[PDB]
Image (cartoon, coloured by chain):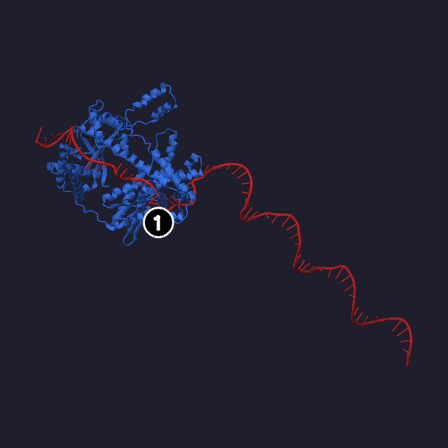
Amino acid sequence: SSQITIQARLISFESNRQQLWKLMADLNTPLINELLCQLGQHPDFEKWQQKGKLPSTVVSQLCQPLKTDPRFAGQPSRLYMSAIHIVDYIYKSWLAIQKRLQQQLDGKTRWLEMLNSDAELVELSGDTLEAIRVKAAEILAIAMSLSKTLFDAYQETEDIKSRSAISYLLKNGCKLTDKEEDSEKFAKRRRQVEIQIQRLTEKLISRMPKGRDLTNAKWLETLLTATTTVAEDNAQAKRWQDILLTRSSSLPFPLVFETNEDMVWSKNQKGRLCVHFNGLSDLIFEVYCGNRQLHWFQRFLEDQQTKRKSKNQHSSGLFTLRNGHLVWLEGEGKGEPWNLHHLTLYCCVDNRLWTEEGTEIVRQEKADEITKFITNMKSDTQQALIQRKQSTLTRINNSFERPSQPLYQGQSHILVGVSLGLEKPATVAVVDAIANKVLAYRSIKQLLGDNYELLNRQRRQQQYLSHERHKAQKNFSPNQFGASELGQHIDRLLAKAIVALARTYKAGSIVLPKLGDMREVVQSEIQAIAEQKFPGYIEGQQKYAKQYRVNVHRWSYGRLIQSIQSKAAQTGIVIEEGKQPIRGSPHDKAKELALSAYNLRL
DNA sequence: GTGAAGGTTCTCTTCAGTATTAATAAGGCCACTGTTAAAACGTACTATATAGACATCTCCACAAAAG
């Protein structure tokens, strides 16, 4: 996770900002909207959902006739390209989501079929429980990936004895068990799977990507319709209401510049770094950044100047800058939108390209990938692709003469396990795995140190700000706020503390748990309990454990994992994934998480 | 004639998914019975511990006959 974003304000005189706003809002965003509409109507759309993959070129092909439609014709080539990238990534995202959800629904539907109680397994096997227990002992002795191997063994073995023995073996977590099945805990575990299947089935009714209408013409024409026309029935009037409540999108889609050299850097005579974008060189924007990021923007000019001095004998494949996003940030107050909103550039950089040693890491990664490509790839334009790839492979050998910082060296036998929990967001154990000894624990309080008071602040603000929103909603007041930025701050403080401890003990890796989807587990567990406690009373079921379900939906385990992954990559510490045990305290969970990831190395 | 804008391709994704070890629970009012200590409280079949109205025997003092 070595890619990170740095940002700066872009400043320019009003006519440059107005011209860019009108390009984005009047042409580029309407084009994106049109591409999303046409792409969702394509005759292959239903087979793209089955593959879960979009064709590499279909957005580019749809955009070609639109580039000369009077609605969209006025744009530079890179703005059409940006619109293509926006639309292509949206569907690459959405088709990947739907594909995995469909696989989850199919997987659990098979499990629901093969989850049979011992009373059902007796009939469906025709064998006594001891007989299927012995047959499961044989099938386990052959399947010795074990879970998948049993799922593979189940499907084509139509022999109901072995098929039931696999069912019995899978019910217990791929192992034998002597103890009797508690019939109500089984019936609950069956009911959980039905709820999960239903909730997956409902999630697969997701909407197609909606776009951003900045005119909101549909709202005003619906208002005129609903006020002067009789609704033909309740369903038309409901559709009218649903439109009238829909909020207006203020801001256009950002521009995306996937060619780092489509940002051209310079220093003006007042000494400020400046940038202009390919196709819009007349609009000079001035960089206004914090000094904590200035060294990156200075590097972008130095990388640009280095390759010009070498007459392009360097490769921009090793430019520290990777891509840019050009974004309008919503301004407070009033004005024309190019005056109200603040133009902001977000630059992706790869942190390894800062140093010379890290650049050598990237160079070999580039060289191996391109040598693979050239070997596997072998038309005129496809031969031109090979020649560009071969030019890259030649030019990445030329050095940028970057700062030298020796790479981190961590001991392979020292690991940090990080236990994640709802009550204690992180707990760490430094384990010496060949010694099987814990070198150090730290609690959440020791990780946060002097910041530990922020953790009670978060809980207190989450309560307070929720209640103030609840009160504000009843007044239709816009003053609705929350603690997300404090929560993000805490997760970043924890990430830095964990990695600093890992560096201090020379740990080779940080071990993080494969939590899965905690929210759908908790939500289906609690619903199965509540349906027994409040039969036929839906509101009673939804009130049951409401605050626990809320707490689990706020638990930011993904954001914390992501923050740890970024900080570890910036110091070259390996991340490993392990299985967090359910037994024990957060300290013991962290220790056994660490040691299991060591033993799982094969 | 260095700089600006614009062109071009990048493959296949029949793969990934489906199993545990699971925590005390996460429901709150209303009324309505029915237990469950455990506190408050009428009164019984007893086990003694006296207090004192009476009955009893004993020791000592007086009239009739004989030398």
What is the secondary structure assignment of the residue under circle 1? Answer: helix
Identify the amino acid type marked 1: Ala
Does the rendering let one see residue A330?
no
**Which corner quadrant of the image does residue A323 belong to?**
top left
- Using the image as rendered, state which of residue A371 and residue A159 is in the foreground: A159
According to the picture, the residue beneath numbered tag 1 turns out to be A137
Q: In the visual, does A100 lie left or right of A298? A: right
Does the rendering let one see residue A417?
yes
- Using the image as rendered, state which of residue A123 and residue B43 is in the foreground: A123
- Using the image as rendered, state which of residue A442 and residue A397 is in the foreground: A397
Count of picture labels: 1
Question: Residue shown at 23%/43% (left/top)?
Answer: A570
- Using the image as rendered, state which of residue B62 and residue A578 is in the foreground: A578
Q: Colour of chain A?
A: blue
Circle 1 packing at 10 Å, graded few (<14), some (14-19), many (20+), is: some
Quadrant holding the N terminus of chain A: top left
**Which corner quadrant of the image does residue A160 belong to?**
top left
Using the image, determine if residue A105 lies above or below residue A141: above
Image spot of residue B34 (x, y percent): 55, 43
Q: Colour of chain B?
A: red
Image spot of residue A6 (x, y percent): 23, 37
Question: Residue shown at 22%/30% (left/top)?
Answer: A58
Image spot of residue A233 (x, y percent): 39, 22
Chain ID for label 1? Answer: A
Q: In the visual, does A311 lie left or right of A500? A: left
Quick one: which residue is furthest to the top in this view?
A228
Using the image, determine if residue B61 lies above or below residue A151: below
Image spot of residue A10 (x, y percent): 21, 32
